[PDB]
Amino acid sequence: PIRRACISIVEWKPFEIIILLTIFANCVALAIYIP
C-alpha cells in the first residue's frame, strides 16, 4: 500500500548515522551510571 511504499524509503544515509549516534549516546549513558 501507500504506507509500505512511503516507509520503504525512510532508510537512507543519515538514518544509519543517527542510529549509530544514538547507540553511542546509550553506551556513554550506561558508562556514566554508577551503582
Image: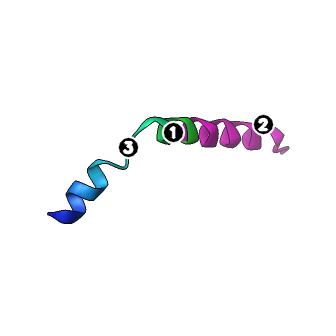
The 10 Å Cα crowd at callout 2, few under 14, some 14 to 19, many 20 or more, is few
The 10 Å Cα crowd at callout 1, few under 14, some 14 to 19, many 20 or more, is few
Q: Secondary structure at mark 3?
A: loop
In the depicted view, which residue is nearer to us: 19 or 35? Answer: 19
Task: From the top left corner, tell me how far across and down residue 27 is, in percent.
Answer: 69, 37
Task: From the top left corner, tell me how far across and down residue 17 is, in percent.
Answer: 55, 35
Q: Using the rendered view, name the quadrant where residue 34 is placed.
A: top right
What residue is at 69 percent from the left and 41 percent from the top? 25
Q: CA distance from mark 2 to mark 3?
A: 29 Å
In the depicted view, which residue is nearer to us: 16 or 35? Answer: 16
Mark earlier in primary sequence (2, 3): 3
- Three-letter code, disc 1: Pro
Q: Which mark is residue 14?
A: 1
| Vertical arrangement, residue 3 with respect to residue 20, above or below | below
Q: Are marks 1 and 3 in contact (CB under 8 Å)?
A: no
- Three-letter code, disc 2: Ala
What residue is at 19 percent from the left and 64 percent from the top? 2
Residue to which mark 2 is pinned: 31
Q: Depth-wise, is mark 2 or mark 3 nearer the camera?
A: 3
Mark earlier in primary sequence (2, 1): 1
Task: From the top left corner, tell me how far across and down residue 18 is, in percent.
Answer: 57, 42
Q: Is residue 30 magenta?
A: yes
Q: Secondary structure at mark 1?
A: helix
Q: Main secondary structure of the magenta part?
A: helix
Q: Using the rendered view, name the quadrant where residue 33 is placed.
A: top right
Q: Which mark is residue 24?
A: none
Which contiguous range is marked in magenta? 19-35
What residue is at 27 percent from the left and 57 percent from the top? 6
The 10 Å Cα crowd at callout 3, few under 14, some 14 to 19, many 20 or more, is few
Q: Which mark is residue 11?
A: 3
Quadrant position of the N terminus in the picture? bottom left
- How many numbered marks appear? 3
